[PDB]
Image (cartoon, rainbow, N blue to C red):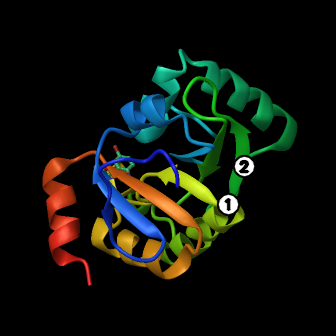
Amino acid sequence: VNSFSGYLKLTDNVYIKNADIVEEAKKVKPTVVVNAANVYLKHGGGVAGALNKATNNAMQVESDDYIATNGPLKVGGSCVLSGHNLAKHCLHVVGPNVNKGEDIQLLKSAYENFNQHEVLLAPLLSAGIFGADPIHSLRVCVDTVRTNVYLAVFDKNLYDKLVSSFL
Ligand SMILES: O=C(O)Cc1c[nH]c2ccc(Br)cc12
């Protein structure tokens, strides 16, 4: 048993809810929250900007030190950093950004990072301002992630569309 509430069950291991991932993280304090990161860990907008704002910018301070030491992530890659006040850990995962012209085929590689963690709270990778089709992102998630993933979908109309189209 775990502390996630009100999720619709999609598969053996994938669950979904219409929720603000910031508010969900604050309530659950999961072991792992996933950030929809970029390779520079520049958290100004979207989930990255919302998560970072909820940490009072401590996520961005930590991330700038990580980049100064290690250099940028790869598209499809990830790193584990602090979860600050939201979670034990934050898994920063870089899905391809279609609006920057990155290869959508890297989405599967991005989701494979989730398999290193038994349970995660996560957004859909490469959807929203990332420019990929969220229906596609959900299909890649279910076909790639084998660990238990709790997906938070911010947009109510998109949540309803994802559930009603899910195969
Ligand atoms: O949860 C959503 O509504 C869509 C979504 C999934 N991933 C996202 C990343 C950024 C932004 Br902005 C939105 C998204």
Check whether the beta carbons of the residues at disc 1 and disc 2 lie within 8 A of each other: yes
Classify the position of the C terminus by image quarter. bottom left
Residue type highlighted by circle 1: Gly
Residue at 54%, 78% in the rendered image: 144
Residue 68 to residue 70: above or below: above
Residue at 57%, 18% in the rendered image: 57
**Horizontal arrangement in the rendering, residue 95 relative to residue 31 (left or right):** left
Residue at 76%, 37% in the rendered image: 67
Residue 158 spot, x, y in % from top left: 19, 57
Residue type highlighted by circle 2: Cys
Residue 60 in view in this figure: yes
Give residue 7's quadrant in the image.
Answer: bottom left
Task: Give the camera-side residue of 155 and 66.
Answer: 155
- List the residue tagged with mark 2: 79
Residue 122 spot, x, y in % from top left: 48, 52
Q: Among all residues in the image, which is located at the extreme front?
A: 1
Task: Give the camera-side residue of 47 and 45.
Answer: 47
Q: Which mark is residue 112?
A: none
Q: How many marks?
A: 2
**Horizontal arrangement in the rendering, residue 56 relative to residue 98 (left or right):** right
Question: Mark 1 falls on what kind of element?
Answer: loop
Using a 10 Å C-alpha cutoff, classify the residue at mark 1 as few (fewer than 14 neighbours), some (14 to 19) or many (20 or more): many
Using a 10 Å C-alpha cutoff, classify the residue at mark 2 as few (fewer than 14 neighbours), some (14 to 19) or many (20 or more): some
> Distance between the Cα atoms at labels 1 and 2?
7 Å
Residue 58 spot, x, y in % from top left: 63, 19
Q: Which mark is residue 77?
A: 1
